[PDB]
Amino acid sequence: VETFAFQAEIAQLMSLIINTFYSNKEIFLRELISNSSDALDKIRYESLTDPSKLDSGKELHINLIPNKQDRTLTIVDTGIGMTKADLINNLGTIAKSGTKAFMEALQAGADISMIGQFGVGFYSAYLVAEKVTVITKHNDDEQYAWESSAGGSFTVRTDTGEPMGRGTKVILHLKEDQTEYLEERRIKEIVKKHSQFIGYPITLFVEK
Ligand SMILES: CC1(C)CC(=O)c2c(C(F)(F)F)n[nH]c2C1
């Protein structure tokens, strides 16, 4: 298990998301589904010139899996997935500029729900989650697990759990007072409101 410090800007963003009073937390789901859609767009496009990129799975979709026993909501996609370099360096580098702009916009009267316009919507996960675990598998790289409970650091390890084929699973370990996001009725409401035109099947799993 390797431990890394967030860039200062991202640590600042995470603290803002965690500490700001903002009741409209439900937008986290729209943001993560949007991320998934983008990742699915990417593998679909790449597969047009290299069909073998789908050897790791032809189906392009999104699953939403609530688990009341673990108090987790998992967003699974079969998108392009992320390399180790993506997890540690690439995405954080691109996120630095978007974070700065988002910060500036907020100071100018924007609100947290506009986070996606700055490309850092993933971090809206911390509106509802005390810890986020990301399991990801890109073609030609290993399956990794990224994890952070904020506090300025994240970890990355090679993942030994069930192999995924290709894609990303975002596991939201929900805050004690945010369990409404495990309810079927609530998730359906949010998907209908904010994600009705996503171009991939979204399956909301039901609890046993
Ligand atoms: C575990 C991540 C790599 C962290 C991160 O920084 C990020 C972003 C961001 F960079 F766009 F914010 N999008 N998706 C992710 C997942």
Image (cartoon, grey):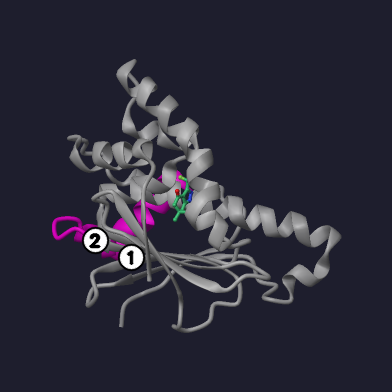
Which label belongs to residue 48?
none
What is the span of residues highlighted in magenta in the rendered image? Answer: 174-196
Query: Looking at the image, is 89 positioned above or below residue 131?
Result: above
Q: Position of residue 51 (x, y in %)?
A: 82, 68
Between 2 and 125, the residue placed more toward the observer is 2
Residue at horizontal 67 percent and vertical 69 percent from the top: 139
Residue at horizontal 31 percent and vertical 53 percent from the top: 153
Between 50 and 5, the residue placed more toward the observer is 5
Left or right: residue 53 compared with residue 2: right
Q: Position of residue 77 (x, y in %)?
A: 53, 64
Callout 1 amino acid: Leu
1 and 2 marks in contact (CB < 8 Å): yes
In the picture as drawn, the residue positioned furthest to the top comes out as 108
Q: Secondary structure at mark 1?
A: strand
Q: Which residue is mark 2?
A: 174
Locate the C terminus and report the quarter of the image it occupies: bottom left
177 within the magenta span: yes
23 within the magenta span: no
- Neighbor class of circle 1 (other Cα within 10 Å; few <14, some 14-19, many 20+) is many
Q: Earlier in the sequence, mark 1 or mark 2?
A: 1
Q: Which residue is mark 1?
A: 73
